[PDB]
Image (cartoon, rainbow, N blue to C red):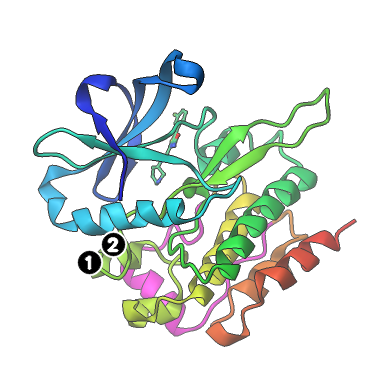
Amino acid sequence: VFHKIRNEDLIFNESLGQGTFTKIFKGVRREVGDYGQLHETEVLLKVLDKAHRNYSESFFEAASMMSKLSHKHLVLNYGVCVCGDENILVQEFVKFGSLDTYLKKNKNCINILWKLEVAKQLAAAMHFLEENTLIHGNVCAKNILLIREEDRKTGNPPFIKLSDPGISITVLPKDILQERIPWVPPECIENPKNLNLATDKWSFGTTLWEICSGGDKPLSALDSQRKLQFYEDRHQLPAPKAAELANLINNCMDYEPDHRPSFRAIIRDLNSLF
Ligand SMILES: NC(=O)Nc1cc(-c2cccc(F)c2)sc1C(=O)N[C@H]1CCCNC1
């Protein structure tokens, strides 16, 4: 199902961080492109920790998810590297990296109309998954990649893409899920089998909170057991200073999954701002 790329066509360079049970690297891919021309393509190389190769089917399923469909806001997958004892995804390389990084570093420079722009693009991506009845399962600012930055001359907005969700929370071990509170919904903490489309509405609300808070991670001062108890007492996240989106956030982060608004409704809400 995955296109096969030979290890000798791939150079592994700098380390770009890690995900849950994964390492990610900037790489270079030599390939034949349109019109027969040879190219050196920057790629993202994503390697599943060999200590955790038992999650490999989830690893590769989460990727084929993003390539079932084609959409302008979904990161492209190029294939899998065929090299022996290893599990390596080859993906589009996004130059400006993760949204959470970019929010922390540019906290000052971001205004309400940049949040709103990014928030809209994300909602358009989620709307598109919605219509296809496709669950992402791991919406968060770190899984949003900045294709391009705002341009203060052309007035052109940033453009973001959504990364694949990684190993699924249906198989991940319980303390990973609990540390992912409050991106993981209450119903999924209670039972990961409760993964639904309404999962992504909650996480979207958490991601909007991240976007309005300049790289702050919600509930970060709270250890695991307190995160759990936050959900027992049915608390809501604090209103972000930039508070234009607090009501939308709370509306998405509804403890009742069936009451979370559709992304069509969310987009209307976002489009009704001055
Ligand atoms: N495709 C691509 O460029 N990805 C990509 C590019 C990143 C990046 C790009 C430029 C500079 C830099 F420091 C990092 S980070 C990242 C990524 O996908 N990170 C994972 C880590 C944890 C959760 N899943 C997101």
Residue on which disc 1 sits? 173
Q: Is 272 on the left-hand or right-hand side of 66?
A: right
Q: Is 135 on the left-hand or right-hand side of 274?
A: left
Residue type at mark 1 is: Pro
The x and y percentages for residue 146 are 58, 37
Secondary structure mostly taken by the magenta-highlighted segment of the chain: loop
Quarter holding the C terminus is bottom right
The reply to whether residue 256 is in sight is no
Badge 2 density bin: few <14, some 14–19, many ≥20, Cα 10 Å:
few
The x and y percentages for residue 169 are 32, 66
Query: CB under 8 Å between callouts 1 and 2?
Result: yes
**Residue at 26% across, 44% down:** 22
**Residue at 60% across, 69% down:** 131
Q: Is 195 on the left-hand or right-hand side of 239?
A: left
Relative depth, front residue between 95 and 177: 95
Q: In this view, does 272 lie above or below 3?
A: below
Q: Give the range drawn in magenta.
A: 217-240
Q: Is residue 127 above or below residue 164?
A: below
Looking at the rendered structure, which numbered label has been put on residue 176? Answer: 2
Q: Is mark 1 on a helix, strand or loop?
A: loop
Q: Label 2 CB, ligand 1: below 8 Å?
A: no
Q: Write down which quadrant ligand 1 falls in.
A: top left
In which quarter of the view is residue 88 placed?
top left
Q: In this view, does 80 lie above or below 204?
A: above
The x and y percentages for residue 110 are 71, 39
Q: What element carries label 2?
A: helix
Work out how far the residue at label 1 is from the one at label 2, CA to CA, in angstroms: 6 Å
Looking at the rendered structure, which numbered label has been put on residue 219? Answer: none
